[PDB]
Amino acid sequence: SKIVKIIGREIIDSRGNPTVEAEVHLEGGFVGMAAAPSGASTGSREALELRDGDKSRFLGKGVTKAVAAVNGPIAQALIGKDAKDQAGIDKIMIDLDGTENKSKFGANAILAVSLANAKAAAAAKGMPLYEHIAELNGTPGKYSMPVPMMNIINGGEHADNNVDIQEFMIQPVGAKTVKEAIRMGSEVFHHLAKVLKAKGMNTAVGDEGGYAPNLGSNAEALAVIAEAVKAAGYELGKDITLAMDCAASEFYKDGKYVLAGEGNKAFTSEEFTHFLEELTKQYPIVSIEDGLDESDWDGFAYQTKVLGDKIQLVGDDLFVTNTKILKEGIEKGIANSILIKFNQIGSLTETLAAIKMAKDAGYTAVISHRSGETEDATIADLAVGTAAGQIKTGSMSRSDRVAKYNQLIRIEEALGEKAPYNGRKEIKGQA
Amino acid sequence: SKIVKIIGREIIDSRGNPTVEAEVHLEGGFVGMAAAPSGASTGSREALELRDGDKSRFLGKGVTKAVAAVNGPIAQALIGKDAKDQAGIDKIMIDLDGTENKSKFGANAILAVSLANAKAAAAAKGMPLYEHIAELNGTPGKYSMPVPMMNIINGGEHADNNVDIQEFMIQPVGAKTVKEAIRMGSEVFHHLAKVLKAKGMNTAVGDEGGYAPNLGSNAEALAVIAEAVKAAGYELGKDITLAMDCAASEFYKDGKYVLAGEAFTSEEFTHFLEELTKQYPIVSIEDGLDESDWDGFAYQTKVLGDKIQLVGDDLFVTNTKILKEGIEKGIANSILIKFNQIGSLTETLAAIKMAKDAGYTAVISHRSGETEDATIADLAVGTAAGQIKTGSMSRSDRVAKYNQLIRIEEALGEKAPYNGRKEIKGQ
Amino acid sequence: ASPELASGKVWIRYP
Ligand SMILES: [Mg+2]
Ligand SMILES: [Mg+2]
């Protein structure tokens, strides 16, 4: 299916910042369109988005350069090529950029085209993206509806409260379909607003559509979530489990973990592991993301020995969707799960490779949004088409989050009996 | 272009509540999909959405009944019909529902199908929705890019502060294209966050993607907006004007207006508003009096209407019977257009036309509960409405409309002029 | 193409 036109444009993301949208047009009239979510433009470890840095537009956050890469050299290199050959398309862009971290054209440019190409190819093949992804994956007809971990309470750098943990999430493991999981999520989300209102706390929402009320401790956040779960008529631990992201790099100083909102105490790597362990005995927390600093591999080795048999230990900053880092982690018994941010790697082909590496090693892959999102819902198709089993795509408000849940609804409706919702067993450590 | 399948489903809106999505499929494969935004389930003046009221699902807010109406009675009535005949398609649904307020099937069911049908027909005709809308409107090839009024600060019932006024908005009138207007909005939006953070105020967002910080008065609210516009490098009154929504019913008591942050008679409240428009470049005032206060509104329109846009929202509820009576009685000079408040594309085109014929302005509006659907962008362009009210510059429920406007302007160029200040009534 | 079709939120069902 020959590519005939590629169009790049600068659109606006859910935080009001520019991002890249691409369209891939094929002979026969087939069109795919996708957008890149927000990412890092500096740093040594992940694929880098290209930003303009022109202070006179969007406070330096323009993406005109990345859009120009799409419309110019990327378009020129891809016109006439076969969109169905995803690896080939991705390789052309990867080689043309020439940098490991896609920092010439920008991972935002390359990813937008990579995804739009895949959508266009699916259309040409008369099938939805999730079906095409399964074919590209060498696992045709193999699907699941992912178990969502849904942002609910924010802290640390993502709030202005005394909660140290960056976010707490609910997982409707007791649901029997993704539609039910979404409804459960919605009901808990609404009951939490009522619970917080009665406490005199603020219920306006953050980037991911959840709450950041002025709670005074990590324990208070867990308690308020438990209360909302009860209010909604669900059973904590059976119907709904908890997941957290510590973003522990945010409190790492001089080789120790200092928690302000815990009386500014300075835990060793081992002590912080046991702090977390105690939380997991007090509440049904079954997944912990970035529970130590990304550099703290000795600490992660210990945390994995102590918690890994019964708790999902998700590397986000730890792995930055990097197969080179993931491979070494696996070799060294570091964590047992990885957050998949496709814009940290920059192409669909490479994203499939990361998901596969995790699965082959018995690690779980959790398909993730970014803080800056769009109306795009490609991660829903990605999670289903690779049968990843889990998704982290926000609270139950803001269409930058809910667009993904709606797409999961459409996909489950279409696939029916062919896309099981497996519930708690998707989570690493849960049988 | 023959309808061969209609599918309704329950999806989730931007506030986490259910709404209706519909697909209309035509012979040859053409498909359109759209969703209803949030609306009213009760009341005697507007079209009503149908809600389930099952306490065990979605706190009683399920839309299974409206979705069933799409999949059953609506589907079978419309299958076989020509999707290009929008008025005919809408007439079938309206007649079948058989009520005056669409309360049998729900305005949510009817609108979702009405819009999805229009998109399907547009696809059959090999054209974008905005182009099809212009043809349906009988104004083929007539377009404009709307001047956005963008939520920026919330107060009243839409906040927990000491601001009486419900909504303050910015209008980037000085922009030359909607793409520029959108950048200007984004820049002011980000500068306001900076200003609020410097004051130790909360910068989390409300339903429309704007801020609702703990401001002590209407005066403080306008002050921070002015500061942000300046910080962004724009001139208030020139590059950017101000619009507001009083929601004046919220302080209406015994025929008087009691603010509790500033007991006005109808005339006295009009002059209170007049005083604000002298002090700040407020050029548009929505629901400046209670919807029932028609003698008050005639007075407000006489006093302010030559120089200020006076937008009926609760006053008109997108109802042409009310708008007609308003026009003849000299009531307001503008109307907010909420397509789910009337319930069909055909009736929406009629409301916009009635407004325009009387010299009133039509402001195409979002609802509090939205989706990623961007139909209102195509609607504003295809009817050359001239103004849009679709949120602050955050949340993709808002920003998806701005993105669609960018896509449309990219295609149309000079064929869809951004006319700026002059779109506003009184300007 | 419509944003719904191009984005892959709706699919063709008929030839
Ligand atoms: Mg993280
Ligand atoms: Mg209003």
Image: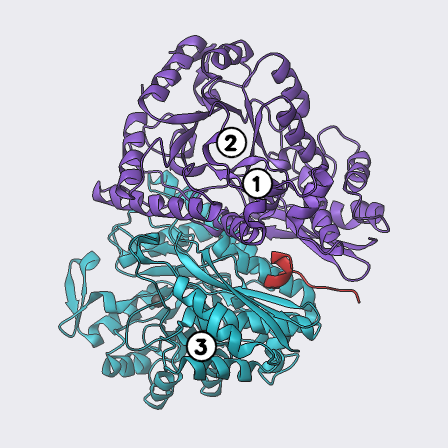
Chain colours: A cyan, B purple, C red
Image position of A201 (left or right of B49): left
Residue at image coords 37%, 83%: A326
Determine whether the residue tagged by mark 3 lies in a helix, strand or loop: loop
The percent coordinates of residue A102 (x first, y second) are 39, 77
Q: Which mark is residue B56?
A: none
Q: Which mark is residue A428?
A: 3
Image position of B179 (left or right of B342): left
The percent coordinates of residue B152 (x first, y second) are 38, 38
- Chain of the residue displaying label 3: A
Q: Is residue A195 in view from this perspective?
A: yes
The percent coordinates of residue A247 (x first, y second) are 29, 66
Q: Amino acid at mark 2?
A: Glu
Image position of B66 (left or right of A44): right
Q: Which residue corresponds to mark 2?
A: B423
Q: Which residue corresponds to mark 1?
A: B144
Picture quarter containing residue A97?
A: bottom left
Q: Amino acid at mark 1?
A: Ser
Picture quarter containing residue A19?
A: bottom left
**Between residues A249 and B408, which one lies in front from this camera angle?**
B408
**Between residues B30 and A204, which one lies in front from this camera angle?**
B30
- Chain of the residue displaying label 2: B
Q: Is residue B250 above or below residue B7?
A: above
Q: Amino acid at mark 3?
A: Lys
Q: Residue furthest right?
A: B80
